[PDB]
Amino acid sequence: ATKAVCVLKGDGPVQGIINFEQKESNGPVKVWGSIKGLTEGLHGFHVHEFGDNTAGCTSAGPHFNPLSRKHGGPKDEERHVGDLRNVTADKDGVADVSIEDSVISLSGDHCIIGRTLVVHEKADDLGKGGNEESTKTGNAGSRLACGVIGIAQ
Amino acid sequence: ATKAVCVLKGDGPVQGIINFEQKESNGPVKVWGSIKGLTEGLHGFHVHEFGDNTAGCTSAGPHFNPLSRKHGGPKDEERHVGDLRNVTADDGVADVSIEDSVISLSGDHCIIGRTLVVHEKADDLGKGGNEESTKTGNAGSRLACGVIGIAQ
Ligand SMILES: [Cu+]
Ligand SMILES: [Cu+]
Ligand SMILES: [Zn+2]
Ligand SMILES: [Zn+2]
């Protein structure tokens, strides 16, 4: 298998760790881990194009989109390769994450290794938002923390 | 003209930015940038196997060595792909500027998604005669490290 990990850090209280795991060549990527310091509710969660943090998460670029598609998230509807929908923070401010994805990958042409993982302020409306914005970012608002996705043991 | 960048963040007063640039695939890689907060003198400078920073820099693993070789200097034939000799600091500042055709931002020796580590001590280039020397050049602990990501 191939493994990756990402330490999410930000300007404020938000911080966490996310693990990625791809058991088979271009198979699904198990994504689990936890993020703390978030306000109760939903937070956009995506992979952006650059693993550049010279300017915090801002320099991370737009959502990872190798196949010029619209933003989204839902099953078989159009989307960006980096759109991981939303993570949920309980009342403690901690969001336990456990999702599985078949579009992202840890090897090949949709490789997310060396790219940034971002957790946002608001919820991602998956592109159901009516306004140019919803098809770009899902109106997920600002970025609270991020990290470069790297190869793990 | 593929590019990569790295922000040597993480605990400590040691912060900096290192850019990686490689025009044509598998060709040389130009490495340059600045680091500050360092102790004066020579500091080992290497690419380690993992971009895992969960427990600070201890989780990056050993040097990025895909050919199973002993630690060495970049001009030695006997080196880890990740060995990039030493960087000098004066006030704790070190201006970096190097080339290396063994590492790469594409293919077999891609350092993307891995960790760039600058050590507390000088790297002895693997000529000590002890195990450490053939593993990390005796460069000491890891003052700072950052995962190498894809830059604009
Ligand atoms: Cu995002
Ligand atoms: Cu090292
Ligand atoms: Zn998107
Ligand atoms: Zn080495």
Image: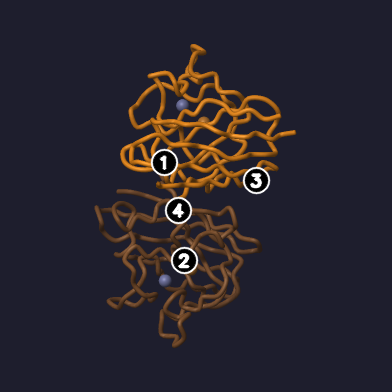
Chain colours: A brown, B orange
The dot on residue A25 is: none
| Residue in the picture at 67% in, 30% down | B89
**Mark 1 neighbour density, 10 Å: few (under 14) some (14–19) many (20 or more):** many
**Amino acid at dot 1:** Gln
Indicate which disc, 4 or 2, sits on the residue closer to the N terminus.
2
Q: Which residue is mark 1?
A: B22
| Residue in the picture at 57% in, 71% down | A142
- Ligand 3 contact, mark 2 (Cβ < 8 Å): yes
Confirm whether residue A27 shows in the render: yes
The chain ID associated with circle 1 is B
Marks 4 & 2 on one chain: yes
**Amino acid at dot 3:** Asp
Asked whether A42 or B91 is in front, the reply is B91
Marks 2 & 3 on one chain: no
- Which corner quadrant of the image does residue B144 belong to? top right
Query: Distance from label 3 to label 4 (Cα)?
Result: 19 Å
The chain ID associated with circle 3 is B
| Residue in the picture at 70% in, 28% down | B40
**Amino acid at dot 4:** Ile
The chain ID associated with circle 2 is A
**Amino acid at dot 2:** Pro
Query: Distance from label 2 to label 3 (Cα)?
Result: 28 Å
Q: Which residue is mark 4?
A: A149
**Mark 3 neighbour density, 10 Å: few (under 14) some (14–19) many (20 or more):** few
